[PDB]
Amino acid sequence: PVSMTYLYNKYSFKLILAEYIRHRNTISGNIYSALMTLDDLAIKQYGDIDLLFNEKLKVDSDSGLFDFVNFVKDMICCDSRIVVALSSLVSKHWELTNKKYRCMALAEHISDSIPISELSRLRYNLCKYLRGHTESIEDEFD
Amino acid sequence: PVSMTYLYNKYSFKLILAEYIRHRNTISGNIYSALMTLDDLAIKQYGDIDLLFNEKLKVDSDSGLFDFVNFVKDMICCDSRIVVALSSLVSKHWELTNKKYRCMALAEHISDSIPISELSRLRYNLCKYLRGHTESIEDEFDYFED
């Protein structure tokens, strides 16, 4: 799922977000490489991500999935680009750690939990970056 | 894995509950056939379980795992019997609905989230049932009273 046609409505944009989160580790296509640039914001919000994951959220634990989601729940409304970056990074970690099943479990929930108006905003700013109007994926409302 | 001595080490028991929840649909052995009888309690507590899963929890939605866990959160200390019956039932459903990944994710969290006191209570009542001392799996405390 790589065509820009997936960017035009809420369902197929959710699919793209879900696919990015599930498969961050191995996924190819410009939409995804663009979304990767969101890491930078996640790093600015929290600091060292490895520290966030290994010492603070304890993401390798039997409860990592739920603790992570819980940590990120107020953010999905406020600023979805932080939570998709962070969700994609944790997913990658779980993938490389033989817990793929969490990748899927997280991706479906986070993508479907982003409120529709925040989702509209994300795609607006995504598309602006993707067609070259903006140096980075911003957070303007239309 | 599974066997009767594995009951009386706490990690070993966490692993049994986890295996039961993960694989309710295919799993074999008496500890597990015994744990299935907890369905009755879940049915007495909530009513028709298909109604619970399909109308109230919307268990097949993209949020089902988290709506399920959220529904069952307060019970993890209060009544582990119910939450293990209900977790294993929703796991079976997910396994049959092409979402095994949810079974895995659920088992690990629920089984590692039961407080150690409640873990003991459950094990004590299960063993009473397993030895034929009890008609069903109860919830008497595993220590003496006052």
Image (cartoon, coloured by chain):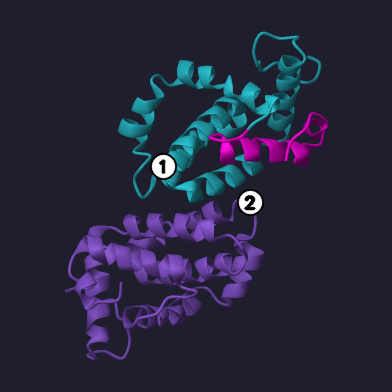
Chain colours: A purple, B cyan
Amino acid tagged 1: Asp
Q: Is residue B131 magenta?
A: no
- Disc 1 is attached to a residue of which chain? B
- Element at badge 1? helix
Residue ID at (38%, 83%): A33
Q: Nearer the viewer, residue A10 or A41?
A: A10
Q: Position of residue B115 (x, y in %)?
A: 68, 36
- Please give the chain letter of the residue carrying mark 2: A
Q: Is residue B10 magenta?
A: yes
Q: Secondary structure at mark 2?
A: loop
Report which residue position mark 1 lands on. Answer: B67
Q: Position of residue B83 (x, y in %)?
A: 55, 30
Q: Residue visible at 64% across and 40% down?
A: B18
Q: Measured along the vertical axis of the image, is residue B94 above or below residue A46?
A: above
Amino acid marked by disc 2 = Asp
Residue interval drawn in magenta: B1-27
Residue at the spot of label 2: A62
Measuring 33% from the left and 86% from the top, which residue is drawn there? A136
Seen from the viewer's position, the closer of residues A27 and A48 is A27
Where on the picture, by quarter, is residue B57? Answer: top left
* Quadrant assignment, res B36: top right
Residue B74 visible? The answer is: no
Instruction: Locate residue A113, reporting x and y percent.
Output: 34, 55
**A114 to the left or right of B47:** left
- Give A40 or B127, whichever is nearer the viewer: B127
Q: Estimate the spatial distance between the alpha carbons at disc 2 and disc 1, rounded to whole Å.
A: 18 Å
Instruction: Name which residue lies at 76% across and 41% down.
Output: B11
- Quarter holding the N terminus of chain A is bottom left
Mark number displayed over residue A86 = none
- Neighbor class of circle 2 (other Cα within 10 Å; few <14, some 14-19, many 20+) is some
- Horizontally, residue B20 falls left or right of residue B49, namely right
Local crowd size for mark 1, using a 10 Å CA cut-off: few (<14), some (14–19), many (≥20): some
